[PDB]
Length: 22
View 1: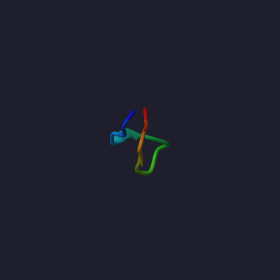
View 2 (view 1 turned 45 degrees about the vertical axis):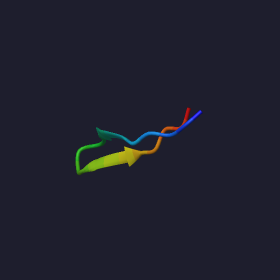
View 3 (view 1 turned 90 degrees about the horizontal axis):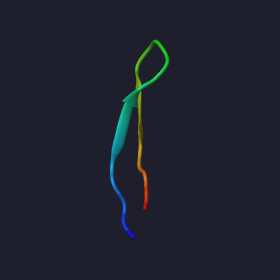
View 4 (view 1 turned 180 degrees about the horizontal axis):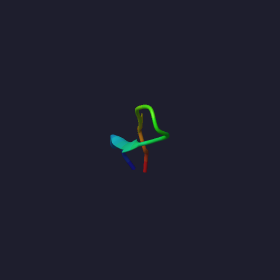
């Protein structure tokens, strides 16, 4: 168990960050 930070470029006007948990 645990969590980690994730990020990636999305669309064509900025990026997005997600917090995956596993």
